[PDB]
Amino acid sequence: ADSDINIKTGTTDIGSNTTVKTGDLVTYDKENGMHKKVFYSFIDDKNHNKKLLVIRTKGTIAGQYRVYSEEGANKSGLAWPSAFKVQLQLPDNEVAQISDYYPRNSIDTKEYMSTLTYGFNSNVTGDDTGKIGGLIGANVSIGHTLRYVQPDFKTILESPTDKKVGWKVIFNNMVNQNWGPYDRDSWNPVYGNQLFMKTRNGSMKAADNFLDPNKASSLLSSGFSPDFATVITMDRCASKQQTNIDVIYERVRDDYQLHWTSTNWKGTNTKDKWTDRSSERYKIDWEKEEMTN
Amino acid sequence: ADSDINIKTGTTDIGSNTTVKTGDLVTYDKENGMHKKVFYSFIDDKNHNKKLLVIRTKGTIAGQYRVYSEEGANKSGLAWPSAFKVQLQLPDNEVAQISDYYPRNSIDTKEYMSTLTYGFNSNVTGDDTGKIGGLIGANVSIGHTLRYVQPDFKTILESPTDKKVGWKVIFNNMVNQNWGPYDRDSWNPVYGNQLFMKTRNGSMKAADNFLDPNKASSLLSSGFSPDFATVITMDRCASKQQTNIDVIYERVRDDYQLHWTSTNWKGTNTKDKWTDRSSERYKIDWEKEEMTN
Amino acid sequence: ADSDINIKTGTTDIGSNTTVKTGDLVTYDKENGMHKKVFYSFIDDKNHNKKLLVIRTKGTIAGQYRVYSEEGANKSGLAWPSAFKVQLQLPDNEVAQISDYYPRNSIDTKEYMSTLTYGFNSNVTGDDTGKIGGLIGANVSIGHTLRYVQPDFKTILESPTDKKVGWKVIFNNMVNQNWGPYDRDSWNPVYGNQLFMKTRNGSMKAADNFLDPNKASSLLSSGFSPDFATVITMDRCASKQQTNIDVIYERVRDDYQLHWTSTNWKGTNTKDKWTDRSSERYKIDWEKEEMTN
Amino acid sequence: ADSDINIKTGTTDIGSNTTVKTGDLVTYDKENGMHKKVFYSFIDDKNHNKKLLVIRTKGTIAGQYRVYSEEGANKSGLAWPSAFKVQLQLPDNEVAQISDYYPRNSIDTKEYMSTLTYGFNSNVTGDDTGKIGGLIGANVSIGHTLRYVQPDFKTILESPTDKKVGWKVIFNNMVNQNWGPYDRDSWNPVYGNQLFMKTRNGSMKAADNFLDPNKASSLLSSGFSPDFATVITMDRCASKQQTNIDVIYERVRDDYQLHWTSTNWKGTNTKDKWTDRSSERYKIDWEKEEMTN
Amino acid sequence: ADSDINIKTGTTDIGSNTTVKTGDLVTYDKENGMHKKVFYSFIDDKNHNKKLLVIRTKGTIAGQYRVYSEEGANKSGLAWPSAFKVQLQLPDNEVAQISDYYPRNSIDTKEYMSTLTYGFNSNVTGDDTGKIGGLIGANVSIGHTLRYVQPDFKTILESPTDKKVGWKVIFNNMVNQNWGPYDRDSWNPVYGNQLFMKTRNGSMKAADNFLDPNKASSLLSSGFSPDFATVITMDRCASKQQTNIDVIYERVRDDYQLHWTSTNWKGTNTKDKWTDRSSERYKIDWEKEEMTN
Amino acid sequence: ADSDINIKTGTTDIGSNTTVKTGDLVTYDKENGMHKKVFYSFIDDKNHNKKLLVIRTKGTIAGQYRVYSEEGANKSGLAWPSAFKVQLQLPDNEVAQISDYYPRNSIDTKEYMSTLTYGFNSNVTGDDTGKIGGLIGANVSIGHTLRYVQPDFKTILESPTDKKVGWKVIFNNMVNQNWGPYDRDSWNPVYGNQLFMKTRNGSMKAADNFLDPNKASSLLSSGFSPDFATVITMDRCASKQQTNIDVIYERVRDDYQLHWTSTNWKGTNTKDKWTDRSSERYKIDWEKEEMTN
């Protein structure tokens, strides 16, 4: 921070004594179930060498956790969201550049513990007969423990360029009724993948053997709300003061099948079975500081 | 945040040097026992591309945890709130759009621990007879631990569009006199669902065998107080500067029945047996910046 | 909050550039032992659609943990506070409405832990007689742990209307000399309820076998200090600018009896034996912005 | 708070752009060892319906933990502070009322844990003789844990009236050289009360067998520093603008006796053996906004 | 705090719109190794009934942990600091009074845990010679745990009067190479006091068997830096506007002796063998608002 | 703090409405690998009785952890930093005094736990023959636990005078591949000191058997960055307004030797074998408020 290098706080920050031009653009893609929102801010600081546009992608991508197929009563299938994506792209002919982005990838930490214990014990034995026994003993024990936090979904900033930035929120693993955690690659010889299996040997039909969406992550059914920031830079004396930008919202859906094996339920997961893409093109006009569809 | 991208704090926020027009609209639905409150704020920031209305839905939906049926002395029934809901809806022909909402769905986390220990031990034995023996041994142990936080009620933002938004607070699980936790699907072959059962084999009438409301969650009896925010956007040069909006408060009630099985009490739960709905229509006047009933 | 929806902090709050008229009304009810204080604030914000009165109920309701009856040396009784209550009520003919209140009911939470461990062990046994034995073994263990916080007293907001709001602070459970915790329904076949029993066996008389108030919760003897806020709304161009409001302080007292059973002490608790009510009527003058008795 | 009911922070607080008249009154009672300090603040807010005087009682009451009697070498006595008290009271004929006080009694909490474990184990045994045996076993375990914090001294607000307020800081229990904790009622059939006993069977005179004051709580020897606030209200157009107020500092001392029982040391405690009182009368002049002795 | 009694923060504090006259006085006592620093602040608030002088005693008292005597190779002695003291004293004839001081004695706390577990277990044993046995068992366990924090040095405000105030920082206990903790009274029949013993039976000179200063508390060798505040009050229209004040820095040194007992090392601690006092007299001129030597 | 003695925050601090003259002096000692940085601030507050110079010593002393000698393949030596030092000294003829410094020595704390458990158990045994046995047992256990934090390096303020101040950062102990922790005095009869030993009996050249610098503290290789502050006072009407000050950066290097004992590696540490000293003289001009080399 500034204080670490003997600088007053906020001294080197952009946007002092500046009129910021903000705006909101709202779209609803009904086919893909995506509520897309762009909150933009034009910052023209005279003390900065460029004009800045801060674009915040927000809204909600619906999860759409849904039983989609029912083959009789012994087979069923569930479509569920394994990844949500948000991407911003500038055409290669533009002179505006992606300058900043938030959030970024963080370094994960773990806690390590080591234990060494040793002990001695003794006992003296007797009975009515009169035989007096005895026992001396010693023991040593070494232990190691590893502790870390596992989120249900991971937020990842994909490798950005000056023309393209993107984030993905991907499924990590989930607890199923205090069991697990299970992920997309969990396998069991008898039950297969038990990610969304409600009962192991219930006598119901397969369509009713999926985990209740209320008992799972709320991102799976109700959906994920992005909050991502991108900063675009522009030269002040450039000839063309118009830019185009593409914003894409994406949802990747996996296919979880349950089938009855005459003795118990078996679950299987197929990755990236479906992809729902929703693209929008926006026009930046830097001169009057506005963003339009 | 702004500071993460070298921007001064609050630079890109709406509502600076603006006169905000606030208001309160209070109604009480006596039949459904709902104290509905709307706190609205009109924000017309010249630097923003649209007019904003922030609507905060507050008040209290009473829980109404109540013994409602007494079939003699061996059977009884309890109505209890399994879900509270708040929905805001714009008519399809309106020009105003739902732009923002709070709270949203968060990603849940869990803590994982793994342990590996190994040890050696030895002992020497003797007695009066002079028999000296010895023992040497080794052991190895692997352990896994999963820790996470479980609320009594979950707040879920249902998948919004630009015309409707909604929240639901749903019953997750509860502790019954240091036992459990129990939820709506808990089942035991002997006792059934023990969610609100006071005693396993008490010799009272069934109407007095339900858990005391003071020993349960306070949401079950006294009720839930919403605090939800939604932001509506409007274009400045629009022909019609009047909007209609519907606000709905909802309570879903489950039916918990206790019956005597000649040896002990058995509990059963039926989901979503009743739904109490309180709908209310408001008129937005964007020019006068007022909300009316 | 405001920052979550891109609004400046405090933008949508009431009370900017407003002269607030505050006042204190103090009364002491000697027969009921209640020090009642009302701290009121009149807020007339021109940008708000109506006039606000914030009423804060404060003061202290004495606990009155007291030995009241001594029948010889074998039977004694103790009166103790099991609930404190504060209620505000508007007459049904008034046009002022209760619009807000604090505190409200919060969602309780708990921590869940699951553990699975497995281990293998072996040992080789020797003897002077040349005996060489061996043992291989394995074990598996599953564990569950539940953690939560239990206060001595619970604060509950009772279901409000637009004319009536109330809070109750009720006894939850208590630790008795590192034992328990015990509550009003704790029962033991030999000792009965041991909530305030000092010793299980004791040659003393029953009046001296009660837990002394210094070792219990301080709310039981010295009392509870309310701090509750209510917001009342008033239309500006209403014909009548006078309101009446009733404030009630209440204490519910249970009866704990100790009796000697020729071998040990037995305790019994009777709920809601006594109720002490203290009611006050106040006059709101909205034009003069004052509150009086 | 104000923000919980949509009010800006500090909107309803007293003392905005007001000239506050502060003062300090210091006295030292040498016989009782009490450094009494009154810090007063006169607040006359035009927007408040009354004049306010905030009186802060500060200072230090010395503990005076000391060996006071030495009967030979087998008996000794120690005087120690079991309670510190601070009381303020107005004469019954005054018009001024006690309106507020701090600190108050808070609700104590405790943490509860319940654990259920079950496991299976097996082993196979052999020797040179060829005798092969086996063992299969199962176990179940239930546990409960209670966690809470115990201060050395408890601060209690005694039940106030409009003319009288008081606080007491009372001895709760303490640790004696990693043993205990012990309190005033601790009893052992062999050693009696071991609260301040240094050694159980040391061969010294009883006057040197008391715990060193440096190893006990510092309140016992160096003393307790009060910090209590009282708010007194006065009507503005009252005829008499003079008030009298009494401030009392109190110390209660217990008597801990050690005596030699020809085999070990035995300690007994007598409660409230001595009381030291220090009273001071102050004159409040509301017109000059001054306070004097 | 002010907010607890509905007062704006900082309303009742001294020093608003006041010119504060600060000053610094530095002395180094070379014989006693004490760097004494007085930071004073004259505050003359017109709204306060007295003149205030805030004196902050700072600097450093060197620990001076050192081997001082070496009698041959079997006996040695180490001088170490067991207490640091700072005292301020006003002459009996002065009119100024000590009114405030910081820090003060606080109340210590501990965490108490109670555990109750019970379990049942069973095992079925087989054998080659058709032998089948069984075992049923049960167990119950009760546990108590006490947890608290032990600092190396305790800071204690000694009982102040209106003429003198004092603090002492005293040695509590220390960990010696992961052993202990040991204090000044620790005794072992074989090794005596092992507070600063490096090895139990090392074959070195006694002067080299003391714990290295870097492995002990840094207060023992490098020393302690006081930071204490005293507030002195003065009447405004007093005839004599000159005060004298004495500031004393003190160090108490214990004597730790090691001697060889032909098999191992034995340590002995003698308390308060040396005392180093450094006294300074300062002159307060209230009219010039200055402090001098 | 000020608020503890009823004084507004920052009332008694130096440097209000003052023009502060700051400066930076950077030098790099290539022979000793020391980047020395002095950040100075002249503060001339009219309300303070003296002129102040705050000097901050910063920069980086490189660790220089390196293998320096390789005698064949069975012996090798590593030079590593065991202490970093920073010293400031005024000549004895100067009238400026060292008045303050930061950081100082803090009091270390530890957490103590004591546990007492007791239990009873019983079992009943039988077999096919018909011998019914029984066992009853009891147990009691006492435990003590000590918990404290151990940094890799300790920062110590050496005993200051009014003419010189110093800090040292010394090596405390380190973890070697999850083993240890080891310090400079660690000794094992077989392996010696294993502080920087990679493998106990690896078959490689001794120069390749040292711990990788990436697996040790980063202070050992990349180095330590001082952040020390000292305040120097000066009289305003002194004759000579020029001061000289010496700033010294120091690194102490230990010698860790590994040698092969025909069966395993043995490590030996020699303390304080090398000392690198970097001295700089600065001229302070109080009239110009500047600092130069």
Image: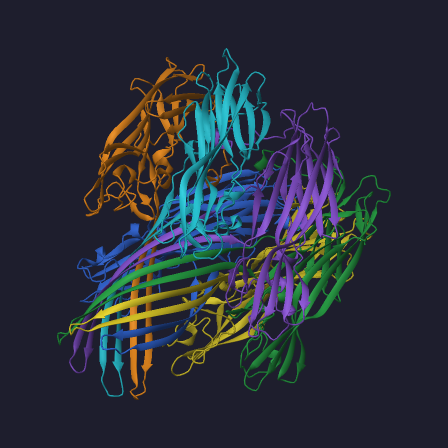
Chain colours: A orange, B cyan, C purple, D green, E yellow, F blue
Q: Is residue E150 left or right of residue F1?
A: left
Q: Position of residue D83 (x, y in %)?
A: 66, 64
- The residue that appears at 60% across and 77% down in the rendered structure is D267
**Relative to the observer, which residue lies in front, E128 or E251?**
E128
Q: On screen, C202 above or below D261?
A: above
**Up/down of E187 relative to C221, above or below:** below
Location of residue A101 in the rendering, given as x and y in whole percent from the top left corner: 37, 30
Does residue C229 appear left or right of residue B214 in this picture? right
Q: For this view, does B3 lie left or right of residue D94?
A: left
Q: Quadrant of residue F187?
A: bottom left
Q: Is residue C180 left or right of residue A222?
A: right
| Depth order, front residue of C115/F18 | C115
Q: How many marks do you count on the picture?
A: 0
Image location (x, y in percent) of residue B95? 46, 16
Residue visible at 42% across and 50% down?
B259
Q: In terms of depth relative to the viewer, which is nearer, A89 or D84?
A: D84
Residue F19 shows in this picture: no
Vertical side of B205 occupied by D152: above or below = below
Residue nearest the observer in this picture, A261 or D179? A261
Task: Name the residue furthest top.
Answer: B239
The quarter of the picture where residue D205 lies is bottom right
Q: Position of residue B177 (x, y in %)?
A: 46, 54
Which residue is at the far right? D239
- Name the image quarter holding residue F276: bottom left
Q: Which quadrant of the figure contains the N terminus of chain A? A: top left
- Residue E247 visible in the picture: yes
Q: Quick one: quadrant of the C terminus of chain A?
A: top left
